[PDB]
Length: 209
Image 1: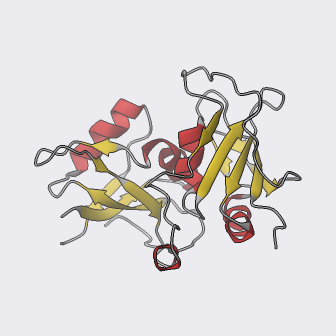
Image 2: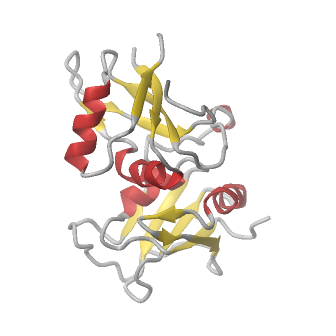
């Protein structure tokens, strides 16, 4: 397998992707430590994972996937680590470089937590969890409208502190694009001070019905 914890991702959409959105997609395959875009390689980012195994899973499931009409090329970087280097401001004001090592949104921080991740191939159906208890289809439609991403074609809430369920799109492409935008959205919490960090992953369910 991979001899480095660092990935190179080519074919990203420069006008839509930032460090958080790269995290939103790659956190499904391992712990993301660093994300770094380079002004010399437009549409490309280095993604440092916790180890080689995370790099293996990420390339196996995301290489040659389409996002915003572009075919992503996910491959092993020749670099052993991401150095902070000459960072720059992206069009949305965020930094080209971001350290996610202390993120509470990383899902592989212990073997126990890592095992709870169902490593699967991208689909047109997303599994959601950590949504507000009383979440509706319309709340997801409003958030998708606000983010300027495609609304899911169907929303299924599972029977149950938080709610979980399924979000379906017409294609794998729509779900992967929405994943990058919607993963970790701060959903309104009427019963407490902290918003609900909506969490997404791929599902093997054929429909949200």
